């Protein structure tokens, strides 16, 4: 069974076969998302991912290997299989390396690299090529809110008119300030009780998040989850902390009008 989507990643750019060429070996790159065929990827039940009738192919299975388009029947079988872990990676099972956008820029060429759970290794398979804009509702039904670059995020009463409560959920698995999309929700370290702040998006593992089935917002590198510190909204501190299932770690997205 097959279905076709765009693949959105770093900075909301899409996986794109360079210059629309279908020549074997043409690299994959980032490019602003659109409907062109070299950005439409068909996911088949054989774990191939195809554009223009050819396969996404690792041109080698080493750290730093380029990913290219290549004829599905003549490519090495190992090199054309991909899986899509629930946290938003795109992994080549043979090598265990993951598809990575090493720079934010358009025309950055995609590589297989060691998985470090970086936001540069986050992807979203979707027909909607725009970030989803939502409030993030958590403990006491309050809303997560940003408060400027380098400052903490924290909880406030939900307001339809508070733009700092509006989050752009980007395809690279970053959570960005909707009005200032260069800025990312960032853990300031990977240890329990490190503080969650807003920092310039830099593709880092500290800027990657996963909304899991238990209502947690998980930082995959650390394993830890967003937590309203001490269940005390007046502290105005959100930290990462091990998942406990407690109310101060439950979150819902609510789409904004
Ligand atoms: C896989 O390729 C990665 C990207 O080139 C390597 O990480 C890079 O290692 C550089 C040192 O050679 C270092 O200056 C870069 O900052 C770093 N880049 C990133 C995005 O992490 C990786 O190298 C290993 O991991 C890094 C973090 C260092 O610890 C290196 O000393 C390691 O060798 C490559 N993996 C391997 C096994 O070589
Ligand atoms: C992938 O490479 C295959 C092997 O070279 C191509 O199949 C070959 O296509 C030739 C010209 O199209 C044709 O003379 C050969 O009979 C055939 N060889 C084999 C082993 O099937 C293949 O081309 C696609 O498949 C063939 C059978 C035709 O349907 C073509 O029109 C197809 O494009 C290459 N696939 C692609 C997408 O280029
Ligand atoms: C989130 O931010 C985006 C990006 O700035 C806002 O989207 C813009 O909205 C204006 C007015 O509707 C449009 O003319 C632009 O086309 C939009 N730009 C983009 C890039 O989408 C959006 O209004 C903000 N708020 C919400 C709720 O999405
Ligand atoms: C909650 O945080 C505030 C602000 O620092 C503090 O005054 C208060 O005593 C804290 N503890 C509880 C139990 O609310």
Image (cartoon, grey):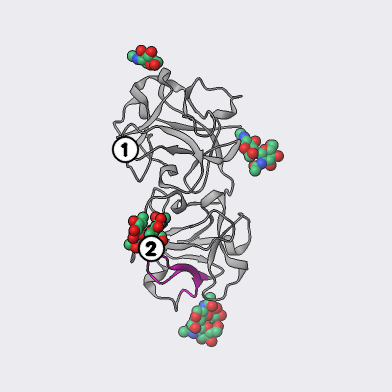
Q: Residues within 10 Å of mark 2 (few under 14, many from 20)?
A: many
Span of residues in magenta: 54-72
- SS for dot 1: loop
Q: Against 107, is 206 above or below?
A: above
- Identify residue for label 1: 191
Please identify the quadrant where the N terminus is shown.
bottom left
* Residue 145: image tag: none
Percent coordinates x, y for residue 214 in the rendering: 35, 36
Instruction: Point out which mark residue 92 bears.
Output: 2
Query: Quadrant location of residue 248?
Result: top left
Residue name at image x 44 percent, y 59 percent? 99
Secondary element at tag 2: loop
Residue 10 horizontal/vertical position (percent): 52, 51
Query: In the image, which is nearer the foreground, mark 1 or mark 2?
Result: 1
N-terminal-most mark, 1 or 2: 2
Q: Quadrant of residue 168?
A: top right
| Residue 64 within the segment the image draws in magenta | yes
Q: Position of residue 183 (x, y in %)?
A: 54, 39
- Say above or below: 238 vs 127: above
Ligand 1 within 8 Å, label 2 CB: no
Residue 26 forms part of the magenta stretch: no
């Amino acid at each position: 069974t097959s279905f076709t989507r765009n693949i959105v990643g770093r900075d909301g750019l899409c996986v794109d076969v360079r210059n629309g060429y279908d020549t074997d070996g043409t690299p994959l790159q980032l490019w602003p998302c659109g409907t062109q065929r070299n950005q439409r990827w068909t996911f088949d039940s054989d774990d191939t991912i195809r554009s223009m009738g050819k396969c996404m192919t690792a041109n080698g299975l080493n750290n730093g290997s380029n990913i290219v388009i290549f004829n599905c029947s003549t490519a090495a079988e190992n090199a054309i299989k991909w899986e899509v872990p629930i946290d938003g990676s795109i992994i080549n099972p043979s090598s265990g390396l993951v598809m990575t956008a090493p720079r934010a820029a358009s025309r950055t060429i995609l590589l297989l690299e060691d998985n470090i759970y970086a936001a540069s290794q986050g992807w979203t398979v979707t027909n909607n090529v725009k970030p989803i804009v939502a409030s993030i509702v958590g403990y006491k039904e309050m809303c997560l809110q940003s408060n400027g670059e380098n400052n903490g995020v924290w909880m406030e009463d939900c307001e339809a008119t508070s733009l700092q409560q509006q989050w752009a959920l980007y395809g690279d698995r970053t959570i960005r300030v909707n009005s200032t999309r260069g800025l990312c929700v960032t853990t300031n370290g990977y240890n329990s009780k490190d503080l969650i702040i807003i920092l310039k998006c830099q593709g880092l593992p500290s800027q990657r998040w996963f909304f899991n089935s238990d209502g947690a917002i998980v930082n995959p590198k650390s394993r830890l989850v967003m937590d309203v510190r001490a269940s005390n909204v007046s502290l105005r501190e959100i930290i990462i902390f091990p998942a406990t299932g407690n109310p101060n770690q439950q979150w819902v997205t609510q789409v904004l009008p």
